[PDB]
Image 1 (cartoon, rainbow, N blue to C red):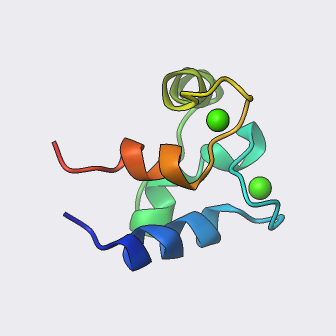
Image 2 (cartoon, rainbow, N blue to C red):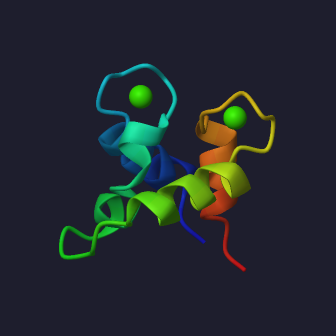
Image 3 (cartoon, rainbow, N blue to C red):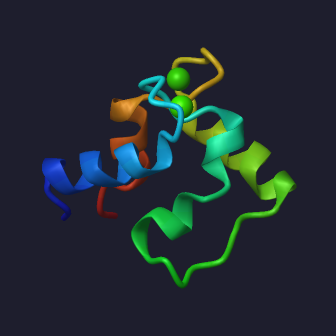
Amino acid sequence: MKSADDVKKVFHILDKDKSGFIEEDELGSILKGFSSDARDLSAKETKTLMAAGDKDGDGKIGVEEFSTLVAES
Ligand SMILES: [Ca+2]
Ligand SMILES: [Ca+2]
């Protein structure tokens, strides 16, 4: 389990425009937020991930939804 501070650090790295949410144009870099040597997601993978992760349906991923995505299974 990653700490809340660690999770927020990655969220901030992904939120390039500081909007407070990860929009579609920022989500493809998600694996890179954790390890710079990770691959980019394809456009199709990004759209799929956005749909799966956007639990409240507002079209973007906020901090709680992002935390849920990375919660330890
Ligand atoms: Ca953003
Ligand atoms: Ca959302």
